[PDB]
Image 1: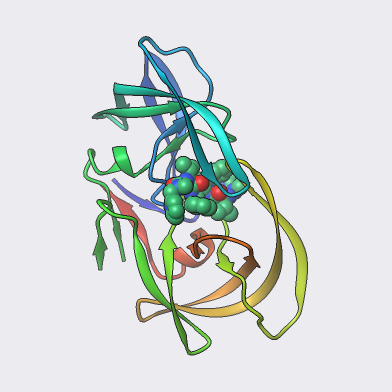
Image 2: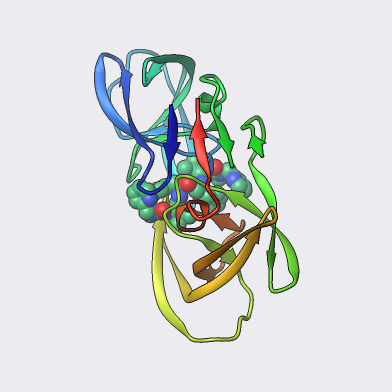
Length: 99
Length: 99
Ligand SMILES: CC(C)[C@H](NC(=O)N(C)Cc1cccc[nH+]1)C(=O)N[C@@H](Cc1ccccc1)C[C@H](O)[C@H](Cc1ccccc1)NC(=O)[C@@H](NC(=O)N(C)Cc1cccc[nH+]1)C(C)C
């Protein structure tokens, strides 16, 4: 689709069989989701932004579906204010900025 | 233009005759710029992100030019690592997300 930015670009994702909403975020390098149990082994990591650093769990090779498009990649899980879809997965689904 | 997301979407902006670089950021509601001393009246404000909150100064009605495109609006100034262009100015330049 083409998404305008008058409101926040929140979409539905599917992951681990759940439905969530997430934010399509060109200002993020990585994907961060709220705390949840995913299958698989994980590594403790840190990530930062405005305000500082949070501890997350890194999950590799996770399948995720974003408005019906599949992406397979790294997800960080942890105490984020909002579910963030970053540039690591936006590129997989062919996302660009246009003006 | 069409900007791809392989790298961070940094573009050149002009603010006050000064050129700078800034991140085009669909996940930010607000525009946030590195410390500088603008003329005009400011409000104190706090904005949040991943690790918590920072203190910023709010300027209103600031003109910025983003890749030859003018936008006018509110800007927050503070101790940010990166200049961030958020949806408040991105919408004015006609910027969309496409996939
Ligand atoms: C999510 C996280 C992995 C990401 N970090 C990175 O991508 N990093 C650290 C890579 C990097 C390093 C050096 C230089 C540039 N990039 C990030 O926080 N990116 C933010 C930009 C930034 C980078 C580095 C250092 C400081 C800032 C931009 C994101 O869009 C971020 C996403 C987010 C939104 C809401 C809550 C938490 C995170 N926005 C923000 O932090 C904005 N907040 C914001 O808009 N709100 C709090 C309102 C809101 C609420 C809900 C939904 C949307 N918006 C700020 C910039 C104003």
